[PDB]
Amino acid sequence: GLQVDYVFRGVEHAVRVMVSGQVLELEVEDRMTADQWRGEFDAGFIEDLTHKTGNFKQFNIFCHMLESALTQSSESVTLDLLTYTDLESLRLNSKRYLILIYSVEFDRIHYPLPLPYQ
Amino acid sequence: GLQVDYVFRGVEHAVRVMVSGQVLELEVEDRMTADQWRGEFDAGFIEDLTHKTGNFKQFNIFCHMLESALTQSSESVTLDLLTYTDLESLRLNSKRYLILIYSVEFDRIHYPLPLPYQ
Image (cartoon, rainbow over all chains, first blue to last red; front, top):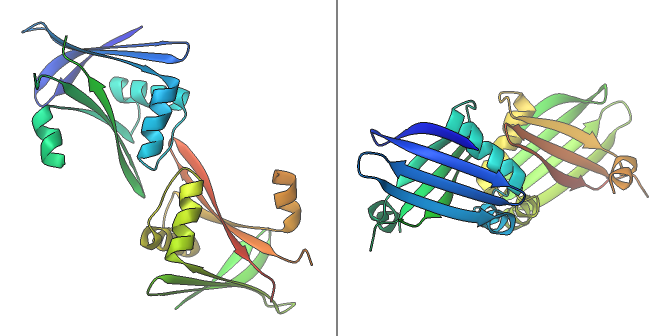
C-alpha cells in the first residue's frame, strides 16, 4: 500500500490508497481529530465516473493518475478535498469528496470520489 | 480564412480552414497534381465525433486545437493525413482522413475528419 501526508486547505491529512485486483480503496484521515473518510471503488464504478465527465479513463490509468497526484510526481494531476458545502454551492453532512483534478492544454477535468465519514 | 503549407508524409500540402458560425470548412490540396480533398462539418457533427473518442471537445475548442496544430503553435496537438489503406489496416478509394492527434500526459486521442476527393 501507499501512505502519504497531503495538505488540503492548509490541513495536513494522512492518505492511504490500496489497489488490489480491480478495486480501489482510499482513506483520508485528520490525525488531530481522528476523523476518517473511507471509500471503496471497483473498476466498473471508476469507468462510469470518468466516462460521465466526458474524459474517459481506464481503471488502471485512473489509479496511476491518483498515485501520481498523491506523490506529486506529475504536472497535470492534482488533488483537492471538498466538503458538502463546496458541492451544493457548485450545484450528517460530514461526507468528503476527494477531487482528482486533471489539467492539460485543452482540458480541465474534475473526477469526484465520494468518501463517507467513518 | 487561414491558409498554411503542411507536410504530410514528406509531401507539402496546402491546407485551408474556414470557421463561420457553427460550421467548419476544410480543404487539403496537392498543388503538383491539383488533387483536392474537402470536408464540411457542423458543430453537431464535431461534438458527436469527439464524444465517440471518449475525450469530448466543444466545437469551438476543437476548431482552436485544429488551428493550433496547423500553425504548430501548441505542443499537444499535431496533424496527419491518412489514406484508405491506413484505415482498413487500422480496422474510388481516393478519400483522405485528416487526423487531429491530441497528445497529453494521460491521453492520446485521434480525431478523424473525412475529406472526400474532389
